[PDB]
Amino acid sequence: YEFAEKILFTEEEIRTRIKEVAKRIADDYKGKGLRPYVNPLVLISVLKGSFMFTADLCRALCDFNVPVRMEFICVSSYGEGLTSSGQVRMLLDTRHSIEGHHVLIVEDIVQTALTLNYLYHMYFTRRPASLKTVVLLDKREGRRVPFSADYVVANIPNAFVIGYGLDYDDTYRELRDIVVLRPEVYAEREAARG
Amino acid sequence: YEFAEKILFTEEEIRTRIKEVAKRIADDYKGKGLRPYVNPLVLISVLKGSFMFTADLCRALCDFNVPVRMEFICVSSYGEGLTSSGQVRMLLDTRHSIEGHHVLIVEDIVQTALTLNYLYHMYFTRRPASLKTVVLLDKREGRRVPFSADYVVANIPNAFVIGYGLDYDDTYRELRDIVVLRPEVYA
Ligand SMILES: O=P(O)(O)OC[C@H]1O[C@H](OP(=O)(O)OP(=O)(O)O)[C@H](O)[C@@H]1O
Ligand SMILES: O=P(O)(O)OC[C@H]1O[C@H](OP(=O)(O)OP(=O)(O)O)[C@H](O)[C@@H]1O
Ligand SMILES: Oc1ncnc2cn[nH]c12
Ligand SMILES: Oc1ncnc2cn[nH]c12
Ligand SMILES: [Mg+2]
Ligand SMILES: [Mg+2]
Ligand SMILES: [Mg+2]
Ligand SMILES: [Mg+2]
Image 1 (cartoon, rainbow over the protein chains, first blue to last red):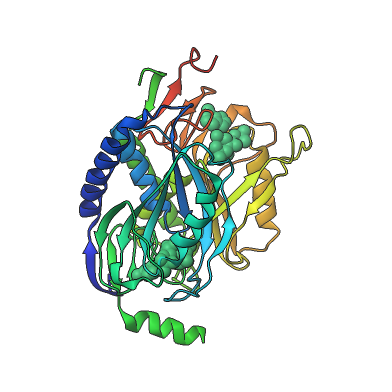
Image 2: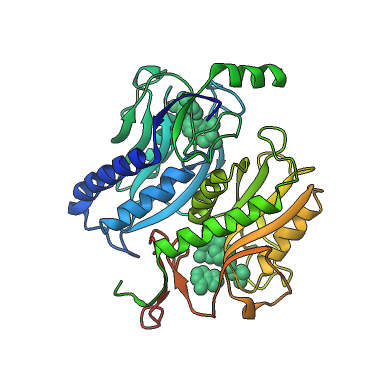
């Protein structure tokens, strides 16, 4: 990748970690007696970024016999930029009610936690049986509001990461690996956009 | 897979065919001058079934250096027996305009093509540079309106398939494989 300063995680590494994480989620939900049709774990995929993690994670969950039901929502905050707008926009909410169900929000990354905080305060009022979160990437020290995800695949530095669903101006989401975008690349774009 | 009467395609077989299709798409757009930011191949993933096919496809397209832009759309029925035309309510449309861009709609399966045909025409009226569709499975004999997909991973008969994004009552989308639902289950 010419635009990458460096590769954080290759596809195999990501695959390996998602497996371990799905195994834990399976052990943790064993006592809930999740079952298809009547008691699936509701996975809430936060678009656009969570699309790839969600696809690979539901399969790893399936490997461990954890029955799921997918809900796709869409929330926007960064837009074409590199930093939080300070605003979280709900572009698409769940199709069904989460009341009484075990819900697990699936996110690609958490930084300021404005997004997950907005989501949690919205969904908690809906009375789900339980509400947890799994984030592929966590920038621990980037919080503007506190938030502790239930499952973190990896902690990372505050630099701008792309690939595997993560974008910079709706680009690079397709990469198989997670990489650090060179500031010179995004700066040229930010400039051209300005 | 106790709930399945038969295995259609294993994860491996699916994986291989998507690569072939992706190489095809790549070659077909070789002269179109695709570039990130300014001229990407816009993928319009039709939720919810194509979510898995799209994740794998965009990565396959990436293997062939085809720069893509992911869009996800969510549609809904207006209310049963209200349209012949396959008209659907748009709950979520493309974030950017497709006008002037090369567009590829991504679907998991097409049978009646009622909705896919409506979606196709809709985006067509938005004046994209080009518009094609890629569907994972094609039940060619089930059409209720004429429609051809430009790229197809596999043609299949009218069996009820599940897995790899495809569901039966919102169940089984997470399977790595595509299998046929036991009629005993769907009864
Ligand atoms: O913790 P925060 O600071 O809120 O940052 C995390 C959010 O920002 C990104 O989404 P974005 O708003 O860019 O939307 P996207 O998923 O469509 O790319 C990321 O995918 C998270 O949803
Ligand atoms: O060509 P057709 O005869 O319409 O059949 C195929 C279409 O319908 C199904 O989606 P569904 O309505 O089940 O939505 P979903 O993808 O969210 O499951 C399937 O996912 C395709 O969209
Ligand atoms: O590094 C990063 N890459 C992509 N999106 C975001 C959001 N927060 N920080 C990001
Ligand atoms: O066989 C099939 N499996 C899953 N969804 C659909 C849509 N049309 N036909 C289907
Ligand atoms: Mg996001
Ligand atoms: Mg983003
Ligand atoms: Mg569908
Ligand atoms: Mg369906």
